[PDB]
Image: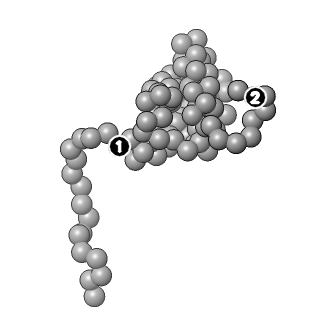
Amino acid sequence: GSSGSSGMGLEEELLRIAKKLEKMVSRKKTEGALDLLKKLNSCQMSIQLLQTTRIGVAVNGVRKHCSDKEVVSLAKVLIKNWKRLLDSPRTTKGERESGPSSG
């Protein structure tokens, strides 16, 4: 589109990031993943986008090709957070006292 970045998009930056990550993973380097991850964290992710940007696999790709803490951490958060965004359809269990207002 027109030159300059100011308005709507995200989906673009998201993809641009993935590519960067995906590339890094491919080249097995991952140097500036944090920066990428960071943005992601500060990028309104969505299920539909999770498929388009396919960043979900990008992050993991790093979290796997990276044993760091910060680069791995943020990556985890991206997974967790996305875990809620996408939260694929699966069965699970877990409950801790189900009773609001008890007293």
Specify the quadrant that holds the C terminus: bottom left
Q: Relative to residue 14, is residue 84 drawn left or right?
A: left
Q: Position of residue 22 (x, y in %)?
A: 54, 19
Q: Relative to residue 34, is residue 94 drawn left or right?
A: left
Q: Is residue 100 above or below residue 62?
A: below
Q: Amino acid at mark 1?
A: Asp
Q: Nearer the viewer, mark 2 or mark 1?
A: 2
Label 1, residues with CA under 10 Å away: few <14, some 14-19, many ≥20: few
How many circles with numbers are drawn on the protein? 2
Q: Position of residue 35 (x, y in %)?
A: 67, 34
At mark 2, the secondary structure is loop
Specify the quadrant that holds the N terminus: top right
**Mark sitting earlier along the chain (2/1):** 2
Q: Amino acid at mark 2?
A: Ser
Residue nearest the viewer, comparing 94 with 57: 57
The residue to which callout 2 is attached is: 2
> Would you identify the image quadrant in which residue 101 lies?
bottom left
Does residue 72 appear in the picture of this structure? Answer: yes
What is the residue that sits farthest to the front in this orientation? 2
Q: Residue at x 27, y 41 (%)?
A: 89
> Would you identify the image quadrant in which residue 14 lies?
top right
Residue nearest the viewer, comparing 46 with 34: 46
Question: Spatial distance from mark 2 to mark 1, Cα to Cα?
Answer: 35 Å
The dot on residue 87 is 1
